[PDB]
Length: 138
Ligand SMILES: C[C@@H]1O[C@@H](O[C@H]2[C@H](O[C@H]3[C@H](O)[C@@H](O)[C@H](O)O[C@@H]3CO)O[C@H](CO)[C@H](O)[C@@H]2O)[C@@H](O)[C@H](O)[C@@H]1O
Image 1 (cartoon, rainbow, N blue to C red):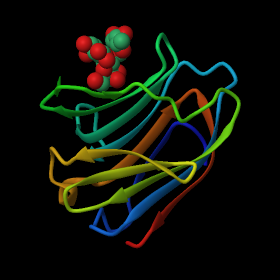
Image 2: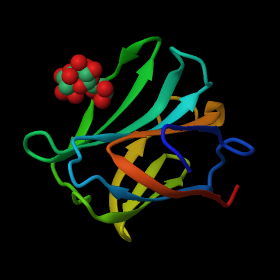
Image 3: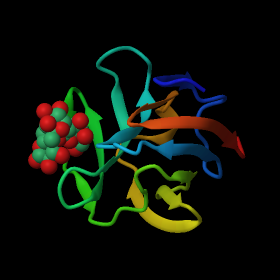
């Protein structure tokens, strides 16, 4: 796949589905993001924004964008990615949350703030190369 990536999720999200992303973090990475989007047009709500950042004390930010407004960020001050390194990034869609798994290691559970049933698109962009995106268990 080429970046930016912004594609419909086949059949939408359902509990039990996984999004499996294989990529390589840029040697000079500052950030990248994965968005679960309600729609495809500019201004669309983002049910789940997953945002690793290497600026400062390395961390991953998690949030939701609704009606043009970012909600209260969640943050985990641990960085499972590495500049220049390949990664395997998995989002397991469960009833209560998105379960994030990185390189086989469970990393975070982000509670749903918008209904998973209303997510239509996946958007990926930033300082990485994308090798593949697969939807499993749809
Ligand atoms: C640093 C910021 O990066 C972009 O905006 C992102 C937004 O930044 C938050 C920041 O994470 C938070 O700690 C602070 O309290 O408010 C900032 C402004 O909203 O965070 C959201 C997720 O919460 C997205 O990642 C945004 O891209 C940029 O647009 C800002 O100008 C600023 O440089």
